[PDB]
Length: 377
Ligand SMILES: CC(=O)N[C@@H](Cc1ccccc1)[C@H](O)CN[C@H]1CC(C)(C)Oc2sc(CC(C)(C)C)cc21
Image (cartoon, rainbow, N blue to C red; front, side):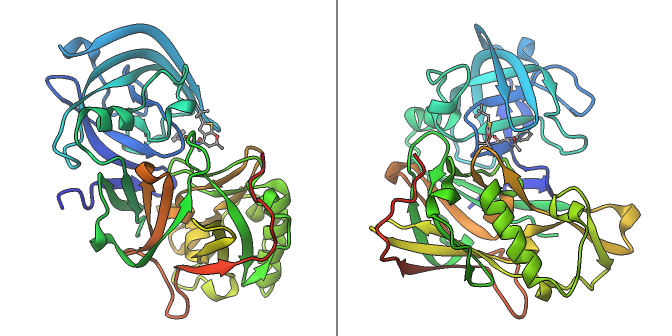
């Protein structure tokens, strides 16, 4: 379809889709964020913005006379709410009127050279700012068009420049192989899921499974890393250390604050373990596992200055706000946000990035006898 390959990005800086806002249409690149629910676009000059939404030029702009403030994990923005016409040139062939936050100030939000000027929050109204009566974009799209209430994401991030597809209203079979496995959306606010087991090199971390979901677990295209609650993060780091102990790395590396570097072409993929995350299935006590390679959790950092080497950041980090299944872990899966059936599907994507020894996988079913609910609260 004309929807394939409509995402672009730079590694670590998010993936974006081209959109238009206003009439006549103004073209902007917009970050695709399943971890939030506000649609906001740069609307005043900023050093890092190539362009921005000029409301004065749009005859369809309607001002809502209400300010809005959104604080994320590090960055934040503030702006003014209004509505306008919005299209996605390489998405469905439709036009919708949607809420739009016109960002007028921000701190640590825009990224120097990222090539996007806005953010599309694809999560549910419950977490929209100022409050849940601010209808999110996807909800407006569904209410206003015949578009089925589902979207899928194939994030590739191949080899600085990355790409992918966002398919709205459907499942494109050309984008995955093998089966689709579904995990229930536990609560419609973030895309909240439940992890029931974690293995490193097939070794179970042996924790009460509530710990994996302390205090929610989410699927978040707007966060780069796999983020893990402290207790789980330290347990994981210990095993991955143990598995790779033929080489020793500085603590700074494990903290995500220092690169590790090897002479180009010589990264020792084989010393690093795979990581399996088992997700609650659609039937009681059944699960499936998604298995991730170090090619996804060792994120390359492109830098012409360090380019006699290949250099990497460790893309697993600690969270005090729950587990976040970020871009790391979505890359090389085809992930189906099936809102209509309150579930999220995972399959191996046409762009999985594997060894001649190992491959990322989505596989099941697994059964557990332990009658314990893994949901935290
Ligand atoms: C790393 C990050 O903060 N990603 C944001 C999206 C973003 C993209 C580019 C620049 C800055 C931010 C993503 O929305 C974060 N997703 C969740 C993650 C969690 C750990 C649950 O923390 C937060 S706070 C938040 C904003 C509200 C939904 C609370 C308004 C969304 C999220």
